[PDB]
Amino acid sequence: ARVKQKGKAGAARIYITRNQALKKLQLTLADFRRICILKGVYPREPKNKKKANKGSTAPVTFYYTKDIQYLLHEPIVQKFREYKVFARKLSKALGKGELETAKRLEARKPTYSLDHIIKERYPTFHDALKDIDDALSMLFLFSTMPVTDKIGAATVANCERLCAEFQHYVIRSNSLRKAFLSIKGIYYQAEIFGEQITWIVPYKFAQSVPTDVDFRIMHTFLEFYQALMGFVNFKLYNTLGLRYPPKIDVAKSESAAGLAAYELEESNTSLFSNFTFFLSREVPRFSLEFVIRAFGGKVGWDPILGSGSPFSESDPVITHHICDRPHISQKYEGRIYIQPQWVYDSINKGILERTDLYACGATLPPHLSPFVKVGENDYDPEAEEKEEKEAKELSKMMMSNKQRKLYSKLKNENSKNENYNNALRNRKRDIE
Amino acid sequence: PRQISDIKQFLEIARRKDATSARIKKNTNKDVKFKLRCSKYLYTLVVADAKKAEKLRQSLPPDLTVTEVG
Amino acid sequence: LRPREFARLSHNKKTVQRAYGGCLSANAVKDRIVRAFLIEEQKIVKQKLKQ
RNA sequence: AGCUAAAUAUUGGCGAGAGACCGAUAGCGAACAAGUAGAGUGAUCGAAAGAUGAAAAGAACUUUGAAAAGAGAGUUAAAUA
RNA sequence: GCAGAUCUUGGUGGAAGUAGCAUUCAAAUGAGAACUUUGAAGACUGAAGUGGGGAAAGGUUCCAUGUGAACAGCAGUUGGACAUGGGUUAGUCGAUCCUAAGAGAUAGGGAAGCUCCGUAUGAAAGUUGCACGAUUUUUCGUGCCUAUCGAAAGGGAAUCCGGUUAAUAUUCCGGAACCAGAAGGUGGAAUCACGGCAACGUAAAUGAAGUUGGAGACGUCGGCGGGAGCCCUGGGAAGAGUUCUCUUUUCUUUUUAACAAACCACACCCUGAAAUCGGUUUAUCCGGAGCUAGGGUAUGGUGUUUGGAAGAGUUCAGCGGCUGAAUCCGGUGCGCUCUCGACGGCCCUUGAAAAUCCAACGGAAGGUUUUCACAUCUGGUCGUACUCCUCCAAGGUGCCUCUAGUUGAUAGAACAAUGUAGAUAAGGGAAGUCGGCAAAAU
RNA sequence: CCCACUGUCCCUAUCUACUAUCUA
RNA sequence: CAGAAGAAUCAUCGAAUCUUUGAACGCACUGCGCCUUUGGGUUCUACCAAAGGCAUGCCUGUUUGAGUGUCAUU
């Protein structure tokens, strides 16, 4: 036969570099990245980088050639090219002083549907439910950010609608399980169709954009997740029988009704069912309304927090009055005054908590993260030497690859953390 | 064909899965030749005393299809 | 050995452990090193005189 | 600067009907086998060769002979087919 | 309307049965044997074969079976004929790949035109030329470098042995290797490894862009050295001779492949400073640009010991496939053949190209690398029969002989004249003929 | 020109093979 | 001849198949490639196979560009 040329097969033929993937697809980096966001594509490092790089050694990212060949026949790529054509016709229309033809061009702007992207990425609904948490984390993060010249106002409006619809489903289906409070925000943990969903909702505050993050990347992730959430919410509402999408009360939204604007008209889940909580004007209503209604508790809130309040301040039906302010001039009776951590501690532990310990002005019991599981020996907040050394310095003496070395991190880090938090109880007892 | 002069490595290469067949040769010089067939190479071992030769017969694994003179 | 058979040899078996080893002779390497140092000194000497 | 049916031509192409034509050395080179067999490095050159009987009923069988065939025989209106 | 045209085509005569075209014996087969087959004898080519192979060319001529219609300057039981079947097996052999002189499409330009000139030419001459980037006003910016054909004799990754067919073998069978590429895995190694004054060594010991170096890759002749095979020959062994006697004698044979392991000698380094010149070639060459001498280093042409491997092959003995043995120790030479090394000339025109492989400088980058070891897998397409400018080539003294191959070329019988060729001849000796033309003389 | 030599010649004779001849 | 029993070496003919070539078109004249997709096997980063593709000139359009070509732009 013929002499096989070196490096014509194997890793050199299976893996493709980023630049060679660019020239193969005839794409630019911004468009190649954008299609890689929408599809499921990512770098893959081979075992032998030098062999896969045709004998070179420069640090170069690798992709599967089969992954790139799958992008050769992507209908979205032709939509990127159609947008380039439209953008140039819009430029010519305005540059020639034809305003009306520019408006017509803007109306027929080429848009693409992510139907087949979702199908080919997530074949089954449970697959989507697995990697749905990252989408929910971002849509809630961007539902509270101000509008920019990078991210539009329509995108922000869609993020609020999709987030509110999902919250309405969880409240309606009582699928919420745990709600945890942290400095980052509020960690929610729910279960849908058996799969576990965990996301984070930040506190509404007038933050500032860090100006170091690239919002072009945020644009494509937002576009992908919004399409993903829309189809997920459509199925979930069909499963419950609710017509999708739920209607939007314009007047209620204009009055900042929050979740109350969207009415879901039909086409230990009862921890707080026999309770009527009240919300003062110092508490995260966007979080307390979600958890309490999800577990059955009826909710009334201060008028300045949003219209559509079923309860008033003077209504005696109030069972508990959540108020984080250290002073309440017009104290009521039969509406025992507690702190917000009381509710979320009750959610985490699945039991009613000590209202006396969580009363206004009292000390605050430590917050327990339900996501943290009890370790082997980690502290939960709520003649031999010769044989030992011989059995401990023989693998580092005789064993071939010394894979026993992993103990130097597995046991070391766990022991150090265990020693610290075990001695912490000794220090706190001594202080007491 | 590597001539092998270490009995112990002849034993370990026999236990290794690459070994397929083994032959024992008795020449006129009262020497015993152990020929082991491997994937690519035929490893031979020449021993001169019968008692060590017999001891290495029973030291060879039973799975190996040893054969006598050809 | 043959040009094709040279590939099978190890890296240390084809090159001598020295600067320019395997491409320039040791005597040539010594002469090249000496000539470069002297030429550098002449450039340094000429620059000082010109300065 | 431009287009345009009919009357007109037609050794080719798809078919047809005829003739004071030739009748196998004739008529096409070729009635069969034909641009074939054959010749030449090649361009090219280029034949000869139609007829058993109505029906194959193409001669069973015997004998001589190594055989090819012969002689009796047989088929046919006739093997002077 | 044919007697003619050196008429055309066909058929057929005399000439005319005319001109003519190194074997022998016995046996077998056959209807039939001067021509077939076997055995014996006698001869012929005589290593430059009538030998054994290939290229080109032919196309089945190769093999087996059948026939004796057409071929057979004769015949056949016979042919290279006819009929029917069989026969060419490759990862390692060739092609395939590369280039040579040249050819040649493309760019352009001619030409009424069939077409011609033109081959990096005033071509926007890049198969995904290459790299960089948290994505760049989600409309791509920055930097770098800038045809094809033509060689079955040139260049080039890799296989040997034994056995096997009616016909095929580096191909098939048995055994034993090798090359290329591919990934992981296991063990080992470094955190971009050490040692030696040095030449350099080792199981490893990253190297981007960019920049070089080497192999490929290079005339011819002569002598010397080395090795292999062949030839010669001393024994040892075996068999077959010859043998009244002599002849420890005559003849014949006496194997180790690819590949894989360990070890085994001119260029350079270190000490050294030399002429009173030393070393030294078959051939006087070198030496303060550092001799002789001492110690090293590398290159291993080779050789040693094995493995392969005796289980194979060959030769003798037997037994009924099996069992025995041996297959040994030398010596060698201006020997022949082939190859390698070290020189010395002559060059002149100072002695192809490319594919391909390796190395150096360089310092981009950072569990990583790892040019160390081991296992695992695959190797497509085409030629392969046979016949024949070139290959292989014994001994002795132009002859003779061995190995090998034929005994065929239409045969028989008679030997007058004729013709050719070859001889001898008394006496004379060129008297022959235009003539010492040819012979003998020397 | 001399010497030697010989079938060139006086003067031809003999032998051998082949040819020539006949037979299939 | 044998053998078979809407037959047929039938006619007609509007549907199909149509090997290698040839204007002959991936490149060559036994071969050598590239691109897209699919498939296989003791068996998968390897190998193999299959299908559909890749000539030149020109025309209409499309997209992407180049120009120290002609300009506009507070």
Image: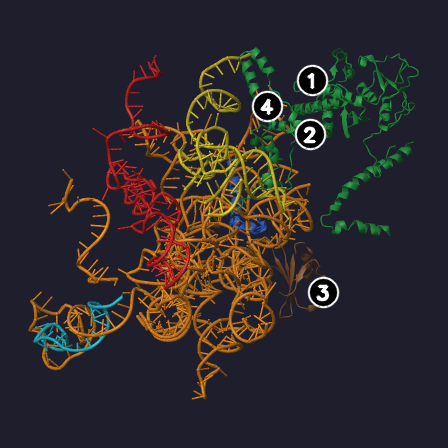
Chain colours: A green, B brown, C blue, D red, E orange, F cyan, G yellow
- The amino acid pointed to by label 1 is Val
Task: Classify D32 as above or below E375.
Answer: above
Q: CA distance from mark 2 to mark 4?
A: 22 Å
Q: Chain of mark 1?
A: A
Q: Residues within 10 Å of mark 1 (few under 14, many from 20)?
A: some
Circles 1, 3 touching at the beta carbon (< 8 Å): no
Please, what secondary structure does the residue beneath circle 4 have?
helix
Q: Residues within 10 Å of mark 2 (few under 14, many from 20)?
A: some
Q: Which residue is mark 3?
A: B55
Q: Residue at x 55, y 19 (%)?
A: A88
Q: Quadrant of the N terminus of chain B?
A: bottom right
Residue E244 lies, in percent from the top left, at 45, 88
Q: CA distance from mark 2 to mark 1?
A: 31 Å
**Which mark sits nearer the N-terminus, 1 or 4?**
4
Q: Is residue A402 visible?
A: yes
Q: Which residue is mark 1?
A: A147
Q: Which residue is mark 2?
A: A122
Q: Quadrant of the C terminus of chain B?
A: bottom right
- The amino acid pointed to by label 2 is Tyr
* Closest to the observer, A192 or E128: A192
Residue E54 lies, in percent from the top left, at 41, 55
* Closest to the observer, E146 or A2: A2
Please, what secondary structure does the residue beneath circle 2 have?
loop
Quadrant of residue E137 in the image? Answer: top right
Q: Residues within 10 Å of mark 3 (few under 14, many from 20)?
A: few
Residue E375 lies left or right of residue A346; in this view the side is left
Q: Chain of mark 3?
A: B
Circles 2, 3 touching at the beta carbon (< 8 Å): no
- The amino acid pointed to by label 3 is Lys
